[PDB]
Amino acid sequence: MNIFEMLRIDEGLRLKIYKDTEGYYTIGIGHLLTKSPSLNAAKCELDKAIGRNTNGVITKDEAEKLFNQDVDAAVRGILRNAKLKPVYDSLDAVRRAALINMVFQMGETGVAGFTNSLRMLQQKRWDEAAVNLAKSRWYNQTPNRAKRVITTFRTGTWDAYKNL
Amino acid sequence: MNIFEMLRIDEGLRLKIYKDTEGYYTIGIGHLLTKSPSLNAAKCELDKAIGRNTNGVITKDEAEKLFNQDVDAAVRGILRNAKLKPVYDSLDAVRRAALINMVFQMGETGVAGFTNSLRMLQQKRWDEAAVNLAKSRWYNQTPNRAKRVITTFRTGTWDAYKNL
Image 1 (cartoon, rainbow over the protein chains, first blue to last red):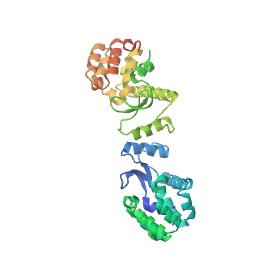
Image 2 (tube, rainbow over the protein chains, first blue to last red):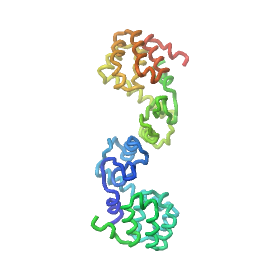
Image 3 (cartoon, rainbow over the protein chains, first blue to last red):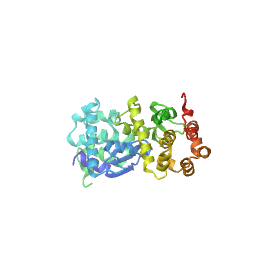
Image 4 (cartoon, rainbow over the protein chains, first blue to last red):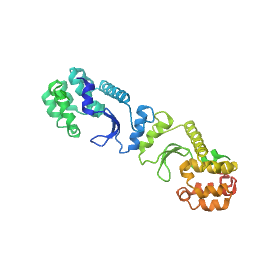
């Protein structure tokens, strides 16, 4: 297990534009196209992301390339951010995947706002961090993935992703 | 006077996205970005049309390139269409500009639907064509330009664009 397998489980794979559970247009492995309610906006953003007139449908290799870029963007965002980098640097490889997962989903700015949870993870207070993360808006926005990500931070194991 | 000067008068020039009188996002010299109500859709379509992240603002040379492409697209659309080509081929240079003007605005499919007006222009019944065009939905959608374009078809002169 690693960050790629973890996110494949949390995001699933689609080759056509679809709306996530919050209503946002998404494609590939969790690639957010726009938060605009406009399908035409999403269709244009897709064409921009891929470099051709896709007519709303991508290939398997195109999905993999976007996923590679999106994971790298999350790591880049962590590394540039003064609140995220120290936490990332302090974590073991499994817990680093849980952090990248959160930034992949919510972005650098969003995750950097989890001030108290970040502090608890840096202090290695795993149980208290898990309790605190479960109070966040994130926990109800995407509950299935949030519970698995929190188990990962709590335990430092892949228990939540076993057999998935 | 020619088609370029004619359209500069009818469309005006803007270097930032604006909405036309029908509410559609437009830029440059009458370059329609989208009929979607979404500004985000329009912003993405602009980036696609130009080939860079424009942040909603283009250069004078970029406006000229889009205008060159858009006039050529209108001529290409006339030449491929069985209802438009015979009319175009029959018209003098001034009246051909009035026809290109209409196709630049409404598209090949749209203008090809003016069955009776097209027939009258091919038959050189200028007065009757002018009366008939003034009954169309186009005449009330964009009345200032429609009156000038109709004068051009009626007279075969540039009278309607003199000093503008």
